[PDB]
Image: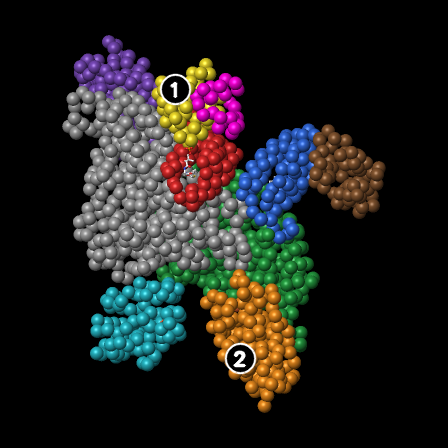
Chain colours: A blue, B red, C yellow, D brown, E cyan, F purple, G orange, I green
Amino acid sequence: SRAQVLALYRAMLRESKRFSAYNYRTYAVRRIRDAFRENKNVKDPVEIQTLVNKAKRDLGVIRRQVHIGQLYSTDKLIIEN
Amino acid sequence: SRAQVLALYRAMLRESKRFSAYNYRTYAVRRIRDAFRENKNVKDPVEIQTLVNKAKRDLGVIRRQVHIGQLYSTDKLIIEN
Amino acid sequence: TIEERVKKIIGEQLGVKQEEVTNNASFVEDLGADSLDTVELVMALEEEFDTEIPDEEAEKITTVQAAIDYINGH
Amino acid sequence: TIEERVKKIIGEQLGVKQEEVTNNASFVEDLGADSLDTVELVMALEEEFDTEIPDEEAEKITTVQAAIDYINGH
Amino acid sequence: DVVNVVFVDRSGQRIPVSGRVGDNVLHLAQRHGVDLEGACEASLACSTCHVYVSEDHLDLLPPPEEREDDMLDMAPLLQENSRLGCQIVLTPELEGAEFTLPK
Amino acid sequence: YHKKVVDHYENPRNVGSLDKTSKNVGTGLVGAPACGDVMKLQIQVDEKGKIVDARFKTFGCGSAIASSSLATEWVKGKTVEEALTIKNTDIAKELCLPPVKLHCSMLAEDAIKAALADYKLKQE
Amino acid sequence: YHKKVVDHYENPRNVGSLDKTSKNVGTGLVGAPACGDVMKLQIQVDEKGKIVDARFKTFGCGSAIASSSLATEWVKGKTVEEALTIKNTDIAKELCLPPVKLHCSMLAEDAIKAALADYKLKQE
Amino acid sequence: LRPLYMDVQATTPLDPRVLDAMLPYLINYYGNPHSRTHAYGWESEAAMERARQQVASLIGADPREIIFTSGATESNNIAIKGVARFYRSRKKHLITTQTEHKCVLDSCRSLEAEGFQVTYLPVQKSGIIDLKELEAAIQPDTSLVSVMTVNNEIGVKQPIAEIGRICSSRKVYFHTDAAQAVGKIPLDVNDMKIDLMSISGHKIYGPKGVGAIYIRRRPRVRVEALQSGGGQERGMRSGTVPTPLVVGLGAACEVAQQEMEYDHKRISKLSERLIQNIMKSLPDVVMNGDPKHHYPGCINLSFAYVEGESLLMALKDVALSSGSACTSASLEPSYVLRAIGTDEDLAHSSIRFGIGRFTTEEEVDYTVEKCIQHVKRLREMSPLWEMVQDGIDLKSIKWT
Amino acid sequence: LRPLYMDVQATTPLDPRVLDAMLPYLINYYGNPHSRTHAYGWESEAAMERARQQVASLIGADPREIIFTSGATESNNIAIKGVARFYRSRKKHLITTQTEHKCVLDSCRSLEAEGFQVTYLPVQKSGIIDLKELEAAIQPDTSLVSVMTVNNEIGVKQPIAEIGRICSSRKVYFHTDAAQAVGKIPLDVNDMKIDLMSISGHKIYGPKGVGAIYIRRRPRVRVEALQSGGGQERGMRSGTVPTPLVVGLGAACEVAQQEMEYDHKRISKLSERLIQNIMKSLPDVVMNGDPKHHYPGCINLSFAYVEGESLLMALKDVALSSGSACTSASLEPSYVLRAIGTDEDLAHSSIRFGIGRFTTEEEVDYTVEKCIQHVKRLREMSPLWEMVQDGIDLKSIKWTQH
Ligand SMILES: *P(=O)(O)OCC(C)(C)[C@@H](O)C(=O)NCCC(=O)NCCSC(=O)CCCCCCCCCCC
Ligand SMILES: *P(=O)(O)OCC(C)(C)[C@@H](O)C(=O)NCCC(=O)NCCSC(=O)CCCCCCCCCCC
Ligand code: FES
Ligand SMILES: [Fe+2]
Ligand SMILES: [Fe+2]
């Protein structure tokens, strides 16, 4: 299931970088990377499947929130210049 | 005037027919039709332009809300069967 | 039957009672309908027959004969 | 220069001090990079150059030379 | 044209003071030493002329001005019988009125 | 609403009436203590001491309709002594009635008892 | 966030110090840190009797710094008698200070008066 | 498949325009309106002040007279308890109606337990108070008079302007609970001489958990604050003001002010349709409340010899409400229908129909058909119907 | 170009997961949770019970012990006033702290006008109450003790467990204001012997206008209801429950339980980063509060010889807060700083920094750089700095005016 996890990681990273807000984008990218690295050595397939399902639900939430934030967007932060 | 107003009417009706909710679809269609019916005999160009601006803003609101409702959709009503 | 379906749609949209509709009656001159009526009649045609009618052909659709020719051709 | 930019991107991604990257250094063995860092490197390559890498071609990108050839070809 | 009023200080002392019609309650205090500050001096901008009017005689006073009410809103220890001393003018109806100074 | 209550309303079991002039029919008609609940419960007895038919009509809540319907089902097929044993506890345990809903079961039991006493009084 | 107040804050004009050990220099220092706004306004009256230079250093809120800058601008190139004509009302009007921040304008007026008094007690 | 919603008196759906106005403050502008040092707080304060102006514009008043609350319950609590506690030294009497909402009635009961004297004015069989009884109930020590504008149970409108004229003649503060009237019937606090008004967000297609109270400044009405804290909202209601909720309230008030005349015409036509179609096909159906002073959006009908919750259970595809004592958690009968002199038999048979902004002729006709069929069914099931059709009078029959 | 947000103590941004949970109930599930006969009410009630269970799981309590409110202000009012009024026949004394939030202090002062006696416990220079003083302040007629968990101005942590064990020994109800501690530090009502707790929705990345109060059921704690009405929320808080708001609050609590261990670690490293870089580059900078019993997310620093509001005005690109009288609408100096023995000179120089879940290293570095340069600029503008560098003593210097 290595390929499935890698594809899910890639999709989660790609969708999170489309966040319009700076805080949400940075937090989502950092949290996804940290969460995937912290579970790198999990061996139990049941726990792996539970983590995969949690990541899928989080990906759906990220897609919806990214789009709705694109619908209602504001100016960039002073640090993004 | 005639051409632009007709095109705006068509776009508003098209966008309103895409509401996921029955409460929102029917009300939007009926309200658009009744408002274009009541403002058919206006002669002042300034009043016409103000009405077109109001309709443009309402079209933007309709597009955003229709998409958000498509993101968070639910079961059809008992009368839609 | 495309003829019957088009006549039914037009009659339901314009209140013509299904007898004042013919193959030579215009939407505005013969039947009582304005441009706002014509827009939803065309939208109802697009709803019943799945076809994205372009604006040019939509303005070309002014009569029942024109609508029937368009639907039969597409 | 594409040659400098690709190596520089790899230097940011893997923390290589800009010295370790060569034209024959692999991502996994030579440098510190698991699959999670390689996915992040491929995405960074897709960002610096607005070229989207297919998954089949992304699998082929395992060394610096593969990325260099892919970028020069496209 | 003499109207007699009673001043109750911050420490519950009734000080009988005699005044005439047309005087200002706030100025009728310092002349007889009742310790009302009235910093703004009838400018309706400080609300340190705060005073409690007796219940019976409160209804006789003319309605407070909008600026007087604006000052009264901020005034500490606000009560339903709270008025501003700078805006109270002695009248024959106000005989026997008692003015209590807020803490 | 509970599955059994919904089923007992949506599917009528013995909704009707029986001839009061008939000697072999006992009729009960009782009412709730603190609400507008009214049940009519009627039982029929054949030549021997067996209940062959029972009909109900209820003005009341859905739970009261369901209680009266279950009461007529349980009454049918028993005798007078076997039907005197039916309690509101059993009716409530069958319908899973919440605490606010025990009045319907008590009213159904009262209707059963009134119908049985009425049968005895007329058969005297 | 008034345009005039931050104008003087981001571009403060006469910030600095002057020689207290000078015959032709008056030094003002009013306010307390416990209160939260302290100003040091210094003037230099020339031989002609007309202020030629002015410097200030202010510890306090932004309106206080704007008031100090405006005071240094206004009292420069004027007579001492003309410098006394400056009131806190004029500074508040110019800076559009809300009633809560009039302490800054009054403090600036006291600083100007203190510098003038220092000159009037030193020139002899 | 979801059922139809005909319960707008309980709560209304959110208007898409209101949600479109709310979302930017739920996504980007999340600052505290009381933060005075940065742009986040500056823009939140600007949005709040605009929302306040919108509410004031709707009710015809000055923006400084508007205080945001968490709902009409808190608005009524503030009005009643604050007025009574502030004017306690001289005024110890309150006047309200027997048909008032439970928040008002419970505040009055608590104040009665607090040593106050409360008079509950009976209503006539039409739901309307007697102005002469109001004038005869006012004492020299009366503090407040509270009469709701539109009744949430039967939908009858009170003579608010006449009541306010009476109260201003007698020098008594007048509070009105307008949670069912704001954005539905014209309201002008100055023409009606209103001193306090309660407003609810989720009755006007706005967000839940937000409300407002109007307090008059000329002549100034004063209240004693109930929520302590840092003196927000001029010291009358402490705690952080929820910016998205107040923005939604302002958007709903503006949308209502624009849509009121069209909505009223549409709802009146639909209410005539529903009432006529129900009456023409079902005998022994009565409308609760007087039709001459009636808001058409709240319809209360009693279906004789049918129980309200059994009818509601039969109508599973329509969301409705009933005054039946069997729908209550505490087995409480309808005190409004007891006040307007309805028999208990017909009070257990009451069904409340709600027609709102998004109600359709399709929904109304479907509800009417379902009601007709299920009432016929339950009447064929009902022993009261049996006895009535069999030439028997309910009153003469003994009941145990 | 919008400024950076570093004011999480005032309010927090809405978490995208919380908004995702809220949106279905703002669009489709608009029913009244108290509607007993139709499906809209049933689904709203189910969502409300789910949110109640989420909050209870976060604070380690039973769901029946959770009552939804409109915020922590209302929760504090309910706790203090209801506990005082319910038991006033025998209990007429209350105990609280001088560094409490204004809702608690104002409720106590409004109870003083009602006939109650209130003791305001002083704090040490660290900001922590002395337990011996609390033990010595308890009377046989003491009703309630109210000590907040995390201070909203300086971020110090009180010994909640010890206070709860003392209150239980003396048979006194214990209330804690945890609006700055929920979802940030571990909380357990049973282990801390807490009888009442206040919770704020928008301090934990939830929606504004919603809160909760925990009321212990065994032993039973009873309050006198403040909001009259239809008897919703166990008769303790009447009115319609705002289903989207309580759903968002529950979602906020569930996210906080999952993310508290990571958030705390990275916020601690960011706070260490900020404090170390400001201290090593600016002399005469003092942190307010004990560094030992401190929550890293709330940092309060005093910059000597620079007024707080001017420094805030300089940092026009960073959203912050101060404790200066000049920032207050009534010229009110910070009473929390006065209670911890901060001299008046440094009270006007205090700046509050807030670090949350959505704060980046780049924001911290940018804020530190801007603060360093602007403090240097303002010190070069200050007369106090000029006198201090001259060798003069500000304390001995008498002040020509006030
Ligand atoms: P056709 O008969 O050839 O042409 C018809 C028209 C109306 C175009 C023609 O009679 C004409 O030229 N009339 C002159 C005046 C005019 O142009 N009227 C229309 C102006 S635009 C208008 O009326 C805007 C209406 C806004 C509706 C808002 C709906 C909001 C819905 C909200 C849902 C949430
Ligand atoms: P690479 O060396 O080839 O390794 C690849 C992997 C990790 C797949 C391989 O080493 C492996 O098989 N490891 C076994 C364990 C494993 O794969 N665990 C991963 C489980 S899925 C996971 O980590 C879920 C992460 C969920 C993050 C949710 C973030 C939500 C953010 C919300 C706010 C925006
Ligand atoms: S003296 Fe200031 S208000 Fe009367
Ligand atoms: Fe019942
Ligand atoms: Fe200042």
User: Is residue C58 on the magenta stretch?
Assistant: yes
Q: Position of residue D19 (x, y in %)?
A: 83, 45
Give the residue at the far bottom of this rendering: G124
Q: Residue at x 42, y 53 (%)?
A: I77
Magenta span: predominant SS is helix
Callout 1, which amino acid? Val
User: Which quarter of the rendering shows the N terminus of chain E?
Assistant: bottom left
Give the residues drawn in magenta, as a range: C50-74
Q: Position of residue F65 (x, y in %)?
A: 31, 24
Residue closer to the observer: A4 or I108: A4
Question: Which quadrant does ligand 3 occupy?
Answer: bottom left
- Tell whether B47 sits left or right of I99: left
Residue at image position (37%, 64%) is E70
How far across and down, in percent of the image, does residue I337 sit? 54, 64
Q: Quadrant of residue I396?
A: bottom right
Residue at mark 2: G83
Residue at screen point 64% across, 41% down: A17
Could you say which is closer to the camera, residue D2 or residue B33?
B33
- Badge 2 marks a residue whose secondary structure is helix
Which numbered circle lies on residue C21?
1
Q: Answer whether residue I389 is magenta in the image.
A: no
